Length: 306
Ligand SMILES: *[C@@H](O)[C@H](C[C@@H]1CCNC1=O)NC(=O)[C@H](CC1CCCCC1)NC(=O)[C@@H](NC(=O)OCc1ccccc1)[C@@H](C)OC(C)(C)C
Image (cartoon, rainbow, N blue to C red; front, top):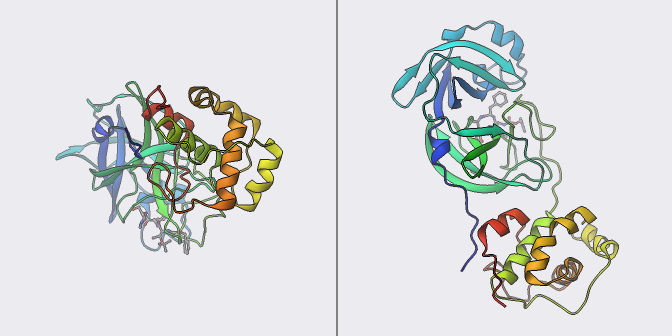
């Protein structure tokens, strides 16, 4: 039946995107109820970017220093505050499209959908994972600040990311919806670089289970392994150490395929040591680590091929 890196339908989120301008800077904002959220760096000027003092720069502005536009309608800002690295703009109107939602701080290794926006207008949607080094490999251009990352459960949108900047390696950094950065990054244009990253072991294992659920067992073997013996091989290939908690999480998938977690680890250990041998898994020539065990169960069918 196939396996794709699919994102959540973006509708509920599109109806919350607005444009926010201050000075000569324009970026996207998130409009929920009667509040608009956006990167606080929107109040910076070319010279302020290197070493800005936001509390100082902010006190120097008023409600009308901010221009908030929803579609082709201007929104009147009647208050403002700073929450960590975000600005909280109160508007005279409550967003009619506000969906049931909540703010969540995603954890490393987890995935979410990003709705790339420009000038308050949604341009695209794609899935990505929060890297262990706290960055994401997105696709953002100037003007994308304010674009958000999210997950959806039933009809509740869990916002978990707002975009703020790009690092030298072409990767991206941002904050949760409370304005707290993911990683040791700060909103200042002083030299910063992503730390060394690692492969998300739990996800690679989840992805292998998905492959089995979809029909092939070519990579499996007759061996098994000690959690400890696996981790020695993990360090060598720069994979995150596997823990008992990770083993526990893979429980349901293990049950649906009848393949013991440690046996799959043995299978992975072999793939890392011998390679793909010119063969593919779910269409890939490399081991994918951007699918959580949750993403697999969500997408795949509850019945394995066999
Ligand atoms: C959202 O509009 C943007 C998005 C960037 C632009 C290109 N792709 C993106 O995702 N906002 C920015 O342009 C930010 C804005 C500043 C953030 C801090 C507070 C003041 C405004 N800048 C970046 O995202 C720049 N990143 C960065 O400076 O990082 C620290 C640093 C400084 C010097 C050397 C290494 C690292 C980007 C434009 O610059 C580089 C591509 C050189 C990293």
